[PDB]
Length: 104
Ligand code: MH0
Image (cartoon, helix red, strand yellow):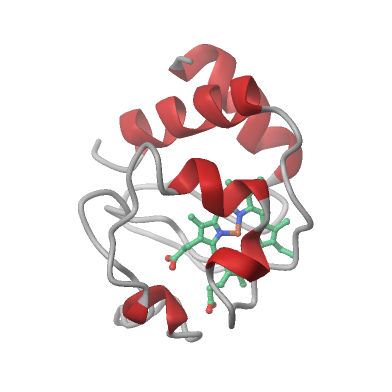
């Protein structure tokens, strides 16, 4: 579960829709800008589906694991078009990379 292993998850499955670039840009999906320590569904340019706001718990290390197991069930109302990440090891490298890049 680290950054260098973890970018090889996001760049493969995710970067086709998302970015993690400082100063922000827009794609099929949001820029992840300061994702950790918050709920989303509200930002000046991002997260237009809002079950992301109403889920009662933040993005963190054991909430992204269970979201990424099956997205449309953990957030029952999202534009996240992705079925689920079968491995927990890959989810753990992915979350590690995002904690380095979203806080940067
Ligand atoms: C484009 C079809 C698409 C792919 C592929 C994709 C992969 C991954 N996502 Fe997505 N994603 C959305 C929301 C999230 C989300 C919350 C972001 C926020 O609220 O700012 C997270 C943490 C996340 N996605 C993570 C991953 C990830 C890792 C991968 C690869 C496994 C939304 C919903 C936001 C909105 O309402 O606009 C969209 C549109 C979305 C698209 C895609 N994600």
